[PDB]
Amino acid sequence: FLKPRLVDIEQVSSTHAKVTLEPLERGFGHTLGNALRRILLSSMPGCAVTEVEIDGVLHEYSTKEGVQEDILEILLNLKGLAVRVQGKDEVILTLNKSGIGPVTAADITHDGDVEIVKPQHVICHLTDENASISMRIKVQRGRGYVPASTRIRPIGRLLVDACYSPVERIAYNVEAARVEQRTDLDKLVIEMETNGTIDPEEAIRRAATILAEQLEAFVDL
Amino acid sequence: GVLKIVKVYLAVKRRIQPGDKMAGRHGNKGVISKINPIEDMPYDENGTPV
Amino acid sequence: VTEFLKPRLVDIEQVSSTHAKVTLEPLERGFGHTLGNALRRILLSSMPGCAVTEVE
C-alpha cells in the first residue's frame, strides 16, 4: 500500500488552511478523509473560555452602567473569542478597560504563554466617560462542548457555556494525484476551518493519533 | 391577614432539548428528537453541516 | 485533554467460522460510527485476497 504524507499545507488565510495528503488508493481517500473530518469535528482540544467574573456585576442577567449591552451579551461575545495557550492547562485573563471605546480582546492583560489570536474580536462597548469594566476571564483547555449546566461557588461568579472546539467547518476533497508514474492514486485535501487556536498541521496529526489509538483495539501499535 | 409578601424572581435559561416543540412559520411543527452531533450532520461539498 | 476512553472487548459472539459478531462497549461519542464506517470501507473495498477472475 501507500502512505499519505504532509505533502503541502496551504495556509490560505489566517483562520483556515488547506492541508494536502498525497499517496492514497481506491477507498482510502474517502475513508481517511471522512474519518479525519469526524475526529476533528468530534474531539479537538480547544481552549475556550468557561468562567467569567465581573468587578461589580452580581449575576448573569444584571447590567452595569456605561456598558453598551447586557452582561449576557458580554458573556456570549466572550465565548466567541479565540484564545490558545501553550504551557498552562488553566489560565486567568484579566481585562481592564476605561473610557469610551469598544473593548476588544487586544486589551486583555495576557500572560507570557496565553495569547489572543483574534485581537479585533469585540467584547463590549464602553459609553460613559467614567465607565470602567474589570473582568477576570477564566480560560481552560478542554475537548468537545460541555455546557455550564452539566458541570461539577460565590454569587459573583458567572458561568459561560464551554465551547472547546477549535474547528468549525471541515471539508475534504478526494482528487487524483500527480505522481511521477502511476494511476489510481488520489490526493486528499482538507479545507479545515479553525478559529485560529490550532495549527492545521498539528490538528491533523492529533486527529490521526486519536483514530490510531481507537484502532489499537484490534491492532498492536 | 398577611404580614409581608416576598417575591423572588428566578431566571431560568432553558436550552434547546430533545422534546422541545419547534415549528416554522408555515405550519410545520415537530418535537426535536435527538441533538445529533455536528460530525454526524449531512454536509455539502463546502463542508458546512446543515 | 488527550485522554480518551479506549474500548475493551466485552463479549464477541462467535457464530460459525464463516460468521462473527464483534462488539465494543466503552468507545466514545460519534467514534462508533467513525470506526464502523472506517473498518467497513477499509475491509470491503481494499483487502489482500485471492479470487477467480477469468475462466476458459
Image: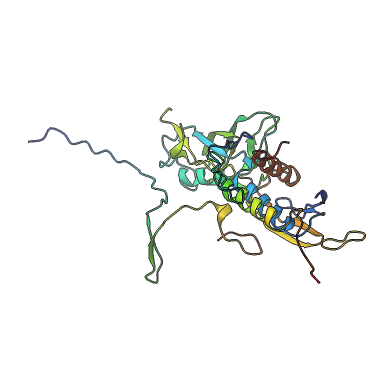
Viewport quadrant of the C terminus of chain A: top right
Q: Residue at x 7, y 36 (%)?
A: B1
Q: Position of residue A35 (x, y in %)?
A: 66, 51
Q: Residue furthest right?
A: A180
Answer whether residue A124 is visible to the viewer in this image: no
Name the foreground residue: A83 vs A186: A186
**In this rendering, position of residue A55 left or right of residue A48:** left
Q: Position of residue A17 (x, y in %)?
A: 74, 53
**In this rendering, position of residue A83 left or right of residue A156:** right
Is A79 situated above or below A25? above
**In this rendering, position of residue A137 left or right of residue B17:** right
Q: Quadrant of residue A29?
A: bottom right
Q: Residue furthest front?
A: C56
Q: Position of residue A78 (x, y in %)?
A: 55, 43
Answer whether residue B49 is visible to the viewer in this image: yes
**In this rendering, position of residue A34 left or right of residue A185:** left
Q: Quadrant of residue A136?
A: top right
Name the foreground residue: B31 vs A78: B31
Q: How many marks?
A: 0
Q: Position of residue A58 (x, y in %)?
A: 41, 34
Name the foreground residue: A52 vs A208: A208
Q: Residue at x 63, y 36 (%)?
A: A108
Is C26 situated above or below B32? above
